[PDB]
Amino acid sequence: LGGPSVFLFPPKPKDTLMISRTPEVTCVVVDVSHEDPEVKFNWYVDGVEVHNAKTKPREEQYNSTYRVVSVLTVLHQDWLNGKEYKCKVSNKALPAPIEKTISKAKGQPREPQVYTLPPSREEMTKNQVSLTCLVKGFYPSDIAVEWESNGQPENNYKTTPPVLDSDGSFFLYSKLTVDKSRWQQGNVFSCSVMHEALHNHYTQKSLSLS
Amino acid sequence: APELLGGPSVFLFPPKPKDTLMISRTPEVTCVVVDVSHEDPEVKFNWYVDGVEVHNAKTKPREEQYNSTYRVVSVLTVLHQDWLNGKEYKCKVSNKALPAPIEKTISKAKGQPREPQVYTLPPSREEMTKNQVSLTCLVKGFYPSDIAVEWESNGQPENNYKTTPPVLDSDGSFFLYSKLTVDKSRWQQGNVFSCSVMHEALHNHYTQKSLSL
Amino acid sequence: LPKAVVFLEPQWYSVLEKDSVTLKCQGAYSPEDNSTQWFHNESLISSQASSYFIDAATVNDSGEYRCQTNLSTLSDPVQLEVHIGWLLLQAPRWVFKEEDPIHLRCHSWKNTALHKVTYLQNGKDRKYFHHNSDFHIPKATLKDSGSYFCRGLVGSKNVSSETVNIT
Ligand SMILES: *[C@H]1O[C@H](CO[C@H]2O[C@@H](C)[C@@H](O)[C@@H](O)[C@@H]2O)[C@@H](O[C@H]2O[C@H](CO)[C@@H](O[C@@H]3O[C@H](CO[C@H]4O[C@H](CO)[C@@H](O)[C@H](O)[C@@H]4O[C@@H]4O[C@H](CO)[C@@H](O)[C@H](O)[C@H]4NC(C)=O)[C@@H](O)[C@H](O[C@H]4O[C@H](CO)[C@@H](O)[C@H](O)[C@@H]4O[C@@H]4O[C@H](CO)[C@@H](O)[C@H](O)[C@H]4NC(C)=O)[C@@H]3O)[C@H](O)[C@H]2NC(C)=O)[C@H](O)[C@H]1NC(C)=O
Ligand SMILES: *[C@H]1O[C@H](CO[C@H]2O[C@@H](C)[C@@H](O)[C@@H](O)[C@@H]2O)[C@@H](O[C@@H]2O[C@H](CO)[C@@H](O[C@@H]3O[C@H](CO[C@H]4O[C@H](CO)[C@@H](O)[C@H](O)[C@@H]4O[C@H]4O[C@H](CO)[C@@H](O[C@@H]5O[C@H](CO)[C@H](O)[C@H](O)[C@H]5O)[C@H](O)[C@H]4NC(C)=O)[C@@H](O)[C@H](O[C@@H]4O[C@H](CO)[C@@H](O)[C@H](O)[C@@H]4O)[C@@H]3O)[C@H](O)[C@H]2NC(C)=O)[C@H](O)[C@H]1NC(C)=O
Image 1 (cartoon, rainbow over the protein chains, first blue to last red):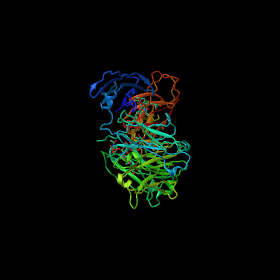
Image 2 (image 1 turned 120 degrees about the horizontal axis):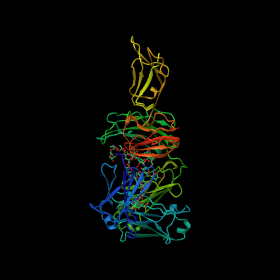
Image 3 (image 1 turned 90 degrees about the vertical axis):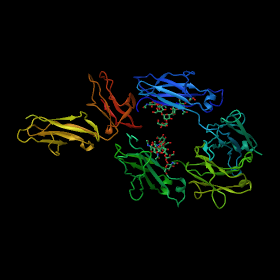
Image 4 (image 1 turned 180 degrees about the horizontal axis):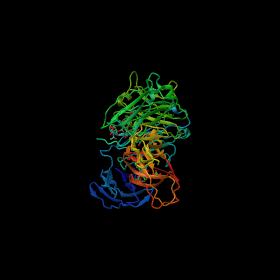
């Protein structure tokens, strides 16, 4: 090999769900000499040239080398429908242009099932309490889960990364903590789940005592 | 074919947590070496237990081709206490196809060892609609990340289950969940199950908790 | 009687192992029996070759090399510095100052293919290269007082050269 390198990035998962968010696949080119800093980007969607579709570039200097960045905004549907996004970078010091395609995970998706699992008496000794919320049978792994406690974004709550199941789907927990008192003296919460399934790529499940 | 201009890399993997914790299990650390030169194979290793070599016994190759290049591995049966104590195991691969040898050194993570806490959680009512509920057991507040987990029902073990790897907890500790897939009935019919947790900070490197209705 | 003179081929005084070096003992010999004497650190060695050939350079082949003959006084000395590595920064001399383009070669063990090579001075990247290539300098300048060392990509793995002081 030897020459400029090219990396293609996809859009942020959450950006691809909230239509109010602007997705964008990014095509970075590194190892751009100071001798031939000319970088020609050509983008292609499902085979045809997107031309501009409003694609944007411009260069900067790091090591002692150059880095250019063209960026194509991805149309939600398109992206979600599995359209393939190709980026063709071609430098002068490049014997033949480099093509990089990226695309949303292939295969039919699956509606993530959410279940709130209250803490265990055995742990009702300690001062804090392990609230939990597993989500399983969803596909793909593109998911985010927060915790609305009082119309707020609670602090100390850890979530695990999805793990492949036997089906083909994935699952993941989300132990949310809270001082005993809180839950103790009867309070409520809910985990937020976002997948490319749910009515509006959104669903929430509540969990309190009783 | 595979051009290899470059020192066939080396990878060294630690031993399995259980094997380390069960005094009847032989934990072996392995030094895998890939990209071995067709025209320059077989390598000489060198294991340095915290300091000194250990040529004697503690050795085990057995070449084996692959993609289009060979692959040699060095197994080294450890010393439970040792390992579980901090012994830094070093491996040094030398192929006449490198300018010099490569030294990889792996050892048990350092930090105040922590005793876990296992809690078993019954599936959520809302899941009863399914033809398989999910017996879920947590495992919080422990360190290091090494640990094993299983499911005892009664006299004999389960398979249908998955576990997420440790996750650094907000308090420098660790944790995880292991979800069990049983059939609607099996659970409902009141059967009993046991989350089998193996870690170092255990009264006997073993604890438990049963889950029933 | 004149002194024999030892020359190097290639002209690189610092080299990697596996490299090939050749020490030639130029000069005149006696018409009656003309053997040459080579001296490694003022000591002999299989005495003959008008051109002692160091075929597979290793660390030990390092030291002061001198040569003599049936009609020459002990040659002046020549230093051969042999190192272990993937890369090596070469140059006739590191003590530079004026009117002379600083020639810096980044050499790779066994001459393997080196790419995306950088030339550094004080842990700072001074020059990048897509494919390995020597690092010269237009007009010598007093602003070249530092510590250099190159590094790049042999295949897909990184390699570096021991540091040096361009004085
Ligand atoms: C042809 O030959 C081989 C094999 O052929 C083909 O096989 C098929 C199946 C295909 O999947 C490919 O494997 C391959 O095409 C091929 O690959 C070999 O070289 C690559 C690198 O070039 C090796 O990659 C490394 O993989 C390890 C993990 O290895 C184990 O775990 C993986 C899990 O994905 C398994 O797939 C492996 O088989 C290994 O198995 C383990 O075996 C142990 C024995 O008991 C066991 O204990 C393990 O549990 C078990 N795992 C299983 C099965 O569960 C990674 O760890 C390496 O990553 C690190 O380096 C990369 C750089 O490449 C970094 O990006 C990354 O960050 C890692 O760096 C480490 O980061 C941590 C912090 O996170 C630091 O603490 C570490 O210090 C740091 N390490 C470093 C870099 O210093 C890496 O990906 C691959 O494993 C090799 N295969 C084999 C035989 O194992 C080979 O490339 C090909 N020839 C050619 C043309 O190149
Ligand atoms: C000299 O310097 C160059 C610049 O590097 C500089 O990095 C910074 C951190 C400095 O501090 C210094 O480190 C240094 O000056 C070097 O360029 C680098 O080259 C190497 C290869 O030689 C590249 O490595 C591969 O990187 C990819 C991806 O990396 C991601 O993560 C790193 C983590 O830090 C980021 O640096 C990087 O930018 C990548 O992700 C991040 O950028 C994306 C694009 O901007 C973000 O995506 C966009 O995000 C937006 C909002 O943030 C928006 O949402 C948009 O929609 C979205 O597209 C992205 O979000 C962000 N982080 C993420 C991921 O979330 C790796 O995948 C790859 O890994 C493997 O590599 C092997 C072999 O290559 C391969 O087999 C595997 O298949 C993988 O590919 C490598 O790690 C590195 O990315 C380059 N850095 C830069 C500038 O991008 C240059 O090489 C140096 N010169 C030399 C050769 O000496």
